[PDB]
Image 1 (cartoon, rainbow over the protein chains, first blue to last red):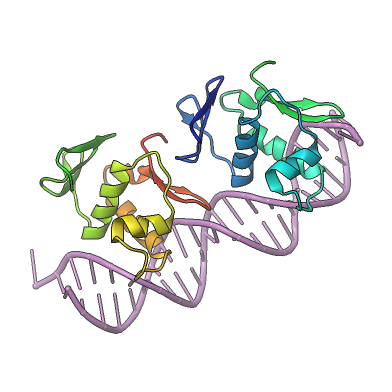
Image 2 (image 1 turned 180 degrees about the vertical axis):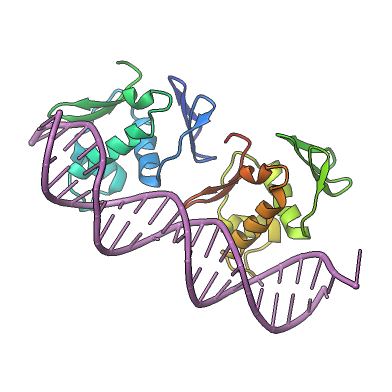
Length: 101
Length: 103
DNA sequence: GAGCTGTCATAAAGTTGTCACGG
DNA sequence: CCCGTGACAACTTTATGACAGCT
């Protein structure tokens, strides 16, 4: 597990930190986990049901639209460096994380 | 307690003298807060759990209670205010504490 | 001319899963 | 499966101010 860097956005597990350039971005633990999954599997879409599975649990109960709300917070928080652009929606399929846009 | 001095954002720990100075002003603080700071500064930009701090600073998690670390982190903070360096003792909710220069 | 420590109980702060509404 | 937001009530994790015993 190393520091993940893309488009000037970094996530270091060790320090447990998210930084847009030299600017650190505050955000709850769920979001950190969310981004941590996206950043580990970029250029791949996931339906909400797959996010709750990969991020919450194969046996978790949370409702599909819960995902949206977290994508949203992960976006409001990825704003300072304009990186919310990387948190991409895919109509009728789910969400994607990508360096392309 | 190694050899050379630790220099960061104007904050410094000199093992040799066993002293902490913000710029040039000395900073007072008990033996532990100093040991903690000595650990934090040699292991920066890396989050540690209260438990690990016990093992590393206290040398063992057996006699003290996890939350005792919060108290010390606080006292270290009050001791780093003068030069404004209390900013480097950062709380990583649900994970512990971390020492960092990037804020 | 004291300076330190480890725990508590308590007040604070930051999170979370859903909703209702709108776009 | 349409998705994105701002608002919530409850819940969980931290920061403090004391406190009494010791070194």
